[PDB]
Image (tube, rainbow, N blue to C red):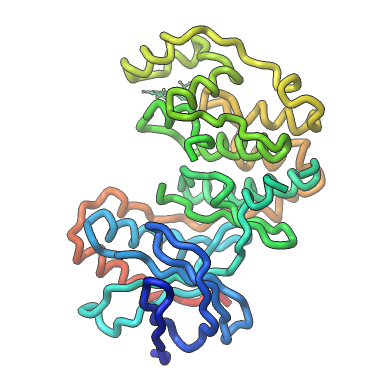
Amino acid sequence: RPTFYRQELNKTIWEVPERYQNLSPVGSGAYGSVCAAFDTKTGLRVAVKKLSRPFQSIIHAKRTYRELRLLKHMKHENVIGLLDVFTPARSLEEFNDVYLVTHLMGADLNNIVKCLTDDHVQFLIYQILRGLKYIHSADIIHRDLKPSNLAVNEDSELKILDFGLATRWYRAPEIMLNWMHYNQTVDIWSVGCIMAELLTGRTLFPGTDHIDQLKLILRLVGTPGAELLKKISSESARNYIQSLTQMPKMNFANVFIGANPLAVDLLEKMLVLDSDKRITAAQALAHAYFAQYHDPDDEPVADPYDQSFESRDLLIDEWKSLTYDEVISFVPPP
Ligand SMILES: O=c1cc(C(F)(F)F)c2c(-c3cccc(C(F)(F)F)c3)n[nH]c2[nH]1
């Protein structure tokens, strides 16, 4: 056990081992607090997230467990992964705080949209796909892909954060409609919204609520055709969709006027209404538009990921304790 030490950071008390010096705040919400820090052990500058109220309820105890499990598993250069996880507690008894350490990045991909040429787009969307491809392959849906959770370095290396746990502007139509069985291509939808915005400077679907959000989607990709109408289970949804004014599928080359044609082509493939026909992350990597970056032996997939716990209803002391085992078994990466 290393030697810890204490300090007050704004509202919160922080108790981090001595290897992290010069804590400084960076942002905080109901995620927890994040500080910037120096890691003496590795020379790296890191982000340290102190979780807010890790075990208030059954749903926070599960959230905490899930998030430790996700971070422990992600090892890929376009996806955040865990440098360290630690607590001040020295037994299960006194365990009430969990800290996660990851590579610092602070800028997010919005902090760029308000500053975006063609090759900059290519490199940025190719990286997101290369990380979705890894993510999807362990059988995980990000579910909330959006500019603010895509972090970029000063040399424009990109990493996905906040995966698996979950702004309406980037959600697929099927989620707006509440479909309970959506597949991984909801993430590819959002990628489609994000590349649009980068090439043009504008939000593609700045819906002002969820009905609006959908009006604006169907305006570009058209109302459902019969092949798709026939796969909708839900009475009420079928009825919703089918009761709007019929809208034709727009020509993307008009709407994206003078974008690279290759880029317009990819969009047209990401933004298919029918989620069964949307391109996949692995197939999009092979698309013409990443001609300059695509390499099939440098686009790895993930180890299997045991998500069997998502269907367990456990006590608050049980997730707490499963988390604890996970903090303990943590083997730092090389
Ligand atoms: O019970 C359901 C409910 C839905 C729900 F998405 F519509 F809600 C669906 C969908 C589905 C998929 C993609 C896009 C759409 C669209 F946005 F075009 F309407 C619907 N496929 N199958 C369903 N079965």
Q: Is residue 245 left or right of residue 316?
A: right
Q: Quadrant of ligand 1?
A: top left
The quarter in which the N terminus is drawn is bottom left
Which residue does the image show at 41% across and 58% down from the upper left? 29
Question: Number of labelled discs?
Answer: 0
In the picture shown, does residue 248 fall above or below 314?
above
Between 21 and 174, the one lying in front of the other is 21
Q: As drawn, which residue projects farthest toward the front?
A: 10
The vertical placement of 198 against 161, above or below, is above
- The quadrant in which residue 54 appears is bottom left
Q: Residue at x 53, y 84 (%)?
A: 21
Provide residue 316's location: percent of width, then percent of height: 20, 62
Among the 4 quarters of the image, the one containing residue 188: top right
Please tell me which residue is depicted at 37% across the width and 66% down the height of the picture. 51
Residue in front for this viewpoint, 227 or 43: 43
Q: Is residue 59 toward the left or the right of residue 218 in the image?
A: left
Task: Provide residue 79's location: percent of width, then percent of height.
Answer: 57, 58
Q: Residue at x 74, y 44 (%)?
A: 121
Instruction: Give residue 237's quadrant in the image.
Output: top left
Q: Position of residue 75 (x, y in %)?
A: 55, 63
Q: Quadrant of the C terminus?
A: bottom right
Q: Residue 295 or 111: which is nearer the viewer?
A: 111
78 horizontally vs 142: left or right? right
Residue 18 placement (x, y as % from top left): 47, 89
